[PDB]
Image 1: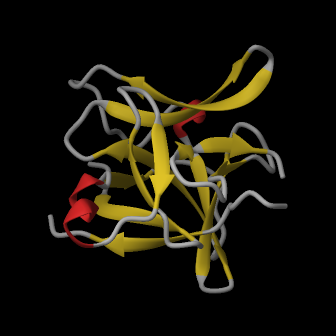
Image 2: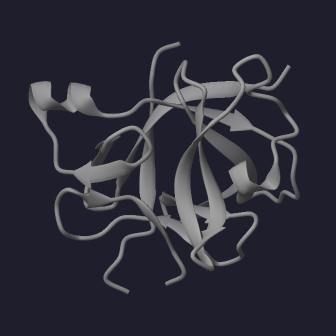
Length: 150
């Protein structure tokens, strides 16, 4: 059965990720009690081409049938949160739209869409803006991961 880890992510400006309605995430500076708003991910280690510093993963919300995915929307590569059938997920052979290449860069991580080369999970420098898929340099594409208890 597919292996997964609970974790949080923060961008390189130490912004945490929170829900923004049902199908979007946003990034903001949180500390103290307000950190509890952050989203916990279940990162699954899925099928795909890999190397030492590039590992295919899927990013689901912990104990929710919701996954980050990359699709064309109005003809542009876009990040979305997508609902799935909870009987069938997670699985090792995730569909390509759900796969990200987790890449080590210096002491940080980037998450490249496997479907759209050189498009990355990104945040803006401004507070309270959506997490999005970026093809680029003001926008932030590097993150750190924090491990969470099972």
